[PDB]
Image (cartoon, coloured by chain):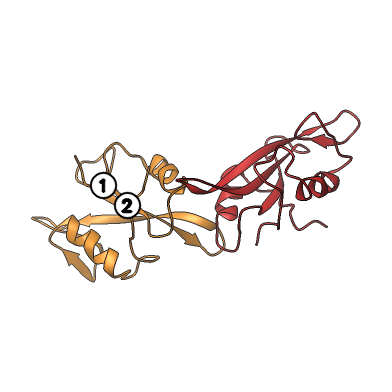
Chain colours: A red, B orange
Amino acid sequence: PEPWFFKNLSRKDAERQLLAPGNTHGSFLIRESESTAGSFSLSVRDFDQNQGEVVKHYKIRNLDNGGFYISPRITFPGLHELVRHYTNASDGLCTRLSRPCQT
Amino acid sequence: EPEPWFFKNLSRKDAERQLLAPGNTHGSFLIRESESTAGSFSLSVRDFDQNQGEVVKHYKIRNLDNGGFYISPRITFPGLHELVRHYTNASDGLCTRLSRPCQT
């Protein structure tokens, strides 16, 4: 039910995908960790200097009550709330989440 | 001392890491030799595979006994430079044409 969720994607694949045409900085995705079902990671397209398109990755960590967080400073009931929060504020992220990875 | 496009101690894996790092665009490239077989070269070029996304294609550079190289049996060159020259100017069957060497 979410356009930015991929799951059966690898770190290297998140980038092959994210760095590909149709994506811009702010482009992002959340995926299922292959060795830890139920734990997730957020990957986002970022562009830096004397370099350019760079894909940044953040571990979404699981709470003991269900829930997630990248930064202990704020938690979210679900991935949905995490994505709503980050699109509306970078809040420690290389940048604000813009559109989902183009498939 | 090799040319800017040629990388000395480079594996396929490390070659890939180089090209996928920031700075490189499609057509960005490098030629490298085989770590376990002397005189065998390969071309690695940053590009994009529909149904995969951004990838590094690897082309096998074959040898003409007694002088010469070729990736395609339809086109041979007397030197590796003429190979890199041709492909910079004419994609000629590769993903696209070689542009700038892999910046590290």
Residue at image point 61% right, 42% down = A56
- Whether pointer 2 and pointer 1 mark residues with C-beta atoms closer than 8 Å, the reply is yes
Q: Does the image show residue A60?
A: yes
Q: Note whether A90 is above or below A99 in the view shown.
A: above
Question: Is A92 placed left or right of B102 in the picture?
Answer: right
Q: Label 2 neighbourhood size at 10 Å, few (<14), some (14-19), many (20+)? A: some
Choose between B52 and A41: the one closer to the eye.
Answer: A41
The N terminus of chain A is located in which quarter? bottom right
Q: Across the whole image, how many numbered discs are drawn on residues? A: 2
Q: Note whether A66 is above or below A14 in the view shown.
A: above
Q: Position of residue B91 (x, y in %)?
A: 33, 69
Q: Position of residue A74 (x, y in %)?
A: 83, 34
The C terminus of chain A is located in which quarter? bottom right
* Amino acid type, residue under disc 1 in the picture: Pro
Q: Which residue is mark 2?
A: B101
N-terminal-most mark, 2 or 1: 1
Please, which chain is the residue tagged with disc 2 on?
B
Q: Label 1 neighbourhood size at 10 Å, few (<14), some (14-19), many (20+)? A: few
Residue B12 circle label: none
Q: Position of residue B68 (x, y in %)?
A: 14, 58
Q: Which residue is mark 1?
A: B4
Residue at the far left in the pictured view? B66
Question: Is A30 placed left or right of B86 in the picture?
Answer: right
Whole-angstrom CA distance, mark 2 to mark 1, is 6 Å
Choose between B74 and A100: the one closer to the eye.
Answer: A100
